[PDB]
Image (cartoon, rainbow over all chains, first blue to last red; front, side, top):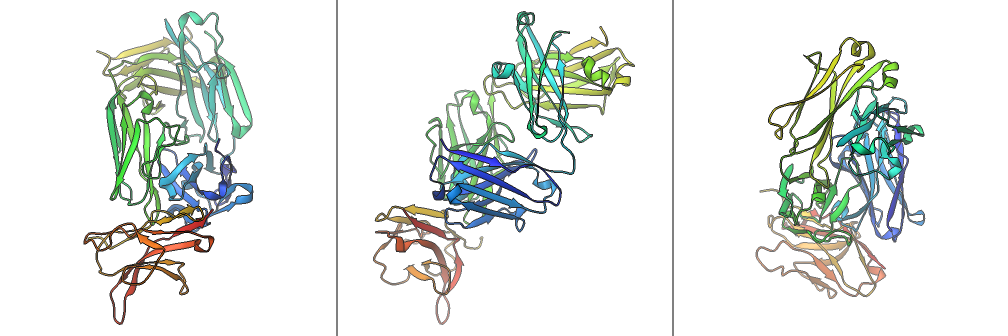
Amino acid sequence: AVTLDESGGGLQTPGGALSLVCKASGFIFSDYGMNWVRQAPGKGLEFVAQITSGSRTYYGAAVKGRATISRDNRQSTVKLQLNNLRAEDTGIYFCARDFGSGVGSIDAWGNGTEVIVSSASTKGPSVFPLAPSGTAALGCLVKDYFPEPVTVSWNSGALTSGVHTFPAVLQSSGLYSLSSVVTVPSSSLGTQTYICNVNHKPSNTKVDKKVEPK
Amino acid sequence: ALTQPASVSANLGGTVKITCSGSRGRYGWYQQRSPGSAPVTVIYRDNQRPSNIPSRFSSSTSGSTSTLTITGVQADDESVYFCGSYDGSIDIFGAGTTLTVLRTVAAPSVFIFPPSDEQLKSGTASVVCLLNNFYPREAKVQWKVDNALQSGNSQESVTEQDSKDSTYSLSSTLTLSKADYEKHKVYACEVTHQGLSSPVTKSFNRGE
Amino acid sequence: EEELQVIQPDKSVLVAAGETATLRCTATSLIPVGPIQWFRGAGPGRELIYNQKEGHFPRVTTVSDLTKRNNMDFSIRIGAITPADAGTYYCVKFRKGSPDDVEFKSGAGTELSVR
């Protein structure tokens, strides 16, 4: 299976620099172009940089002069160096493989990694219940965390049907908040336990909250 | 630059087209189900479909334009589709076309949640109103506290169109200090949507 | 009318030894008049690979008929590829001049490598 595993993202200092690294496997790495593509909050895909199988390099206008892309064929890695970071560089960055015609020839995408250019500090979430009051709704309010992302699951992945996890909102404190809700049969409230599992990798924290009537 | 429309809609089982223009290069079409999630390539290198992609996706390219066709639209085809191309000078993505799957009107199911005792002890009350599984997307929510309309102290978030039943859900959160929360009794969320013949209000009495 | 552009849509082409490489190029206008040529490399030491106006290039065939009035396709196929063919190929528009034709616009180049 083609894999493109990204690292080096997370919180960064305004004016500082970062090195993203993508480690590829499952294909002949030296035959493909490798790309970095990013997406800022509320915006579309934006081209960052590409290095061809022949080691020619291309940069998007917004990073020109600040970015350097390189590859190491022996290690199957591609690296993106980006300096003098500013807020406009905050976003999710994806590694992607191309067949030789640049961004119109991408056939595989990494899962993406959050890059956040900010002086703010990391803070783990508080998780509160949204208690159920024949379909009932219940949930977890995941409040006051930074940076993004958190992920939420229910009953460790066994409950997926009827789950909605809302996009995070930014509060004036500088922290994020989201809710995850699920609808369930009223008749299951007595017997079935419901636990939201909230992962916040940036603070090395996971919180499980069991959500109960009343 | 690449130009593609902001939005297109189709019926379940219908055929839809999305046209992108501005490059004489090769075009790729990249499906993204929610912002920040890994795109999935549906077509690349003009007209090639990766083996795991259903045959309902096809594309044509000629001159300085490319058209994605989806024949037999499914609910899981709801997404933003980005065109991308190297035009012989620069690598560019279009701004994305959102595909909405049309369906019948569904009124929201409305739920209100008081703040937890744990949060209140910490000094803040978040009251949450949930508008679940409605269609179409347009909806309005108002908060009233002892019948006074609230302003300035709420935030809303909405899901993407659901990949199975083609509905939307929305949450609105009213955020108050503990001391403010404790000055009033009746907390109510009022919802307006075209599936309702008149607005629905859910409410609770603080404490009870 | 927008200025002529020379579009090479492929950054990299990978070809098995002995097979044919296809090197794509489109010119976006017929103005100004003048031939298209292909080179390997971009130095003053670049090697001529194909010249629309004249010359003998036994391993090169053109994808389209360049004598057609509306032709904008300058793509070529190079036969019997070997490792000595590896390099970067540029499709280049010339205009007419005195005493001779002058380079007007180059494509961005396509890498040819051999497996």
